[PDB]
Image: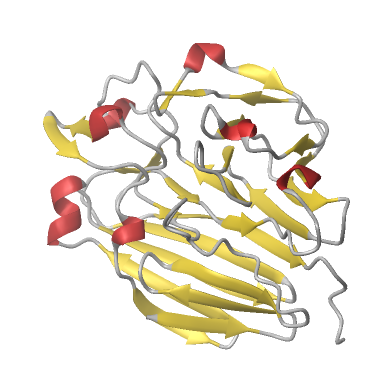
Amino acid sequence: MDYTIENNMIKVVISDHGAEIQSVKSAHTDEEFMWQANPEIWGRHAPVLFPIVGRLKNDEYTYKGKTYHLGQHGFARNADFEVENHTKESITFLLKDNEETRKVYPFKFEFRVNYNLMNNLLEENFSVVNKSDETMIFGVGGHPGFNLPTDHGENKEDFYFDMHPSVTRVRIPLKDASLDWNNRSLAPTDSLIALSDDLFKDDALIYELRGNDNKVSLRTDKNKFHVNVWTRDAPFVGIWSQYPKTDNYVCIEPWWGIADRDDADGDLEHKYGMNHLKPGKEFQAGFSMTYHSTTDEVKL
């Protein structure tokens, strides 16, 4: 089921299936900001990643000596959430553990995804409450896909991303869906990086983030199009688009979790970059997105 939150600036449609944004449109220009999930390329819009971000080696892990099987980015995106609260400019989806999640993930939890509007700014906020009698181990992340508009002669290579603060950051390369740890290197994120079909030939660009002032701007100097993602305290951000079958979108993925390292031992308790949450406690994270059309955000 789809649900709408909206104001005078932007209108957002979100599904209770995976608590996933389906659509973000300018109230002024009717421009669509979200990738529309063409199944020929990538049949999702903006998945929620939980209780892991990225892939486990062999899609498996052990916990307390027992082996579990869990696919890339966990189960949230295939789960149906309850609508806990819904007002004009806010909606909160809730997912609890059930018989099925417990089979692949031996924890009890309350996972809430809240979306709310402030002008042309949309928050995507995560809340995880551990309901288990032991410390819960999880990753959580966003994965919004944004259109690159090409209705007025623009091309993907006219677009770029720019990270603020403008500092060089460590990139963690991916090899066979695991972190190619020993090839981490400082990357030229102190200035813009242009998009292209070939850019993502070696999978997602993964950057180590520091502090809480990080913002990734997706822009073009052809027009006024501008999507800004404020990653708050995310320790990582992934930038990705499909390859070898390409299309005109890019994902900017704030992550509080990360794929297995090439050398992971598979023990969940040893898994690098996971959050550890004591019984009864709450973890909160999230990020914010602002949208600007190719033209002015004014009444025409």
Furthest-top residue in this view? 182
Q: Is residue 213 above or below residue 48?
A: above
Q: Position of residue 297 (x, y in %)?
A: 84, 76
Residue at 23% across / 61% down in the picture?
A: 97
Q: Is residue 28 above or below residue 46?
A: below
Residue at 51% across / 11% down in the picture?
A: 182
Any part of residue 280 in sight: no
Quadrant of the rendered image containing residue 273: top left
Q: Nearer the viewer, residue 234 or 22?
A: 22
Furthest-front residue in this view? 153
Any part of residue 150 in sight: yes
Horizontally, residue 66 falls left or right of residue 118, namely left
Horizontally, residue 272 falls left or right of residue 101, namely right
Q: Which of the image's four quarters has the C terminus?
A: bottom right
Q: Which of the image's four quarters has the N terminus?
A: bottom left
Horizontally, residue 295 falls left or right of residue 20, namely right
Q: Position of residue 87 (x, y in %)?
A: 53, 87
Residue at 25% across / 34% down in the picture?
A: 59
Q: Nearer the viewer, residue 228 or 31?
A: 31
Q: Position of residue 216 (x, y in %)?
A: 72, 46
